[PDB]
Length: 261
Ligand SMILES: *[B@@]1([O])O[C]C2=C1[C]=[C][C]=[C]2
Ligand SMILES: [Cl-]
Ligand code: NA
Ligand code: NA
Image 1 (cartoon, helix red, strand yellow):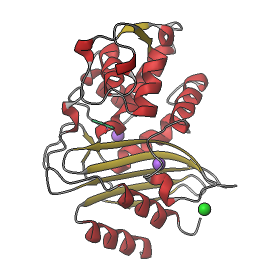
Image 2 (spheres, rainbow, N blue to C red; image 1 turned 60 degrees about the horizontal axis):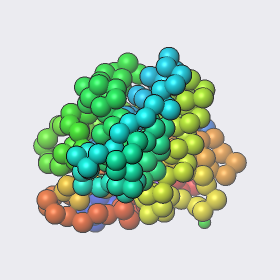
Image 3 (tube, helix red, strand yellow; image 1 turned 30 degrees about the horizontal axis):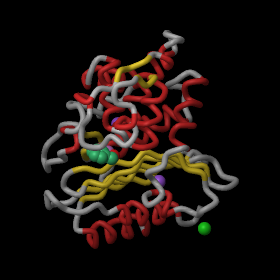
């Protein structure tokens, strides 16, 4: 109740629309705020694409070593790793790491293409029991985040439950689960988001997202000091098409829902 009042106050001050889902595995409890509303995932969808590749690799052992050509024609709007590999190849493992740890959009497109496209990533989500996630488009258009548009959205509740399954549950084989967690723990883009609202000693694997309408997102698995793990999704979007990012709102939400732990 106090947590709910604090999240509502944060949302009001922010000017936008805030979605939160915390799962606390210590007691199997949740804290939810707009957790059944849809939000544009933006780059947080890269977790599902990498997980789909990891699942495929369980029955294709050479898969992560498979080479993928990077061409000038593959470049999109944000290519921090891929732009260094034009005219060479990258492995699917390298593309997964680049997508998850640098939010590289060429890398995401290669993961999407490899598994068969956005509808295949979506079908993988369905196979896991997530009937909310939808990936409609490739990069860069999947980030438009237009209000009222259900494309490329999920809900905080669904993403938290699915991220729990992927990182702490049994969606993936042990090797593949460990690889996903290792990749997320090595993310370079999340220090101002959920991490900024947690004590410095806590260990975080997260994936951020940003897009149109000032959309600012983060999804995380969290190992608090001497506590059972948490899963936290913080999604945020704003009324103005050119609104600036608000990572501070995600940090504030993370602090609110973990205060007392
Ligand atoms: B994703 O939300 O993370 C960084 C980025 C994304 C999409 C488009 C451009 C950059
Ligand atoms: Cl601290
Ligand atoms: Na989801
Ligand atoms: Na973070």
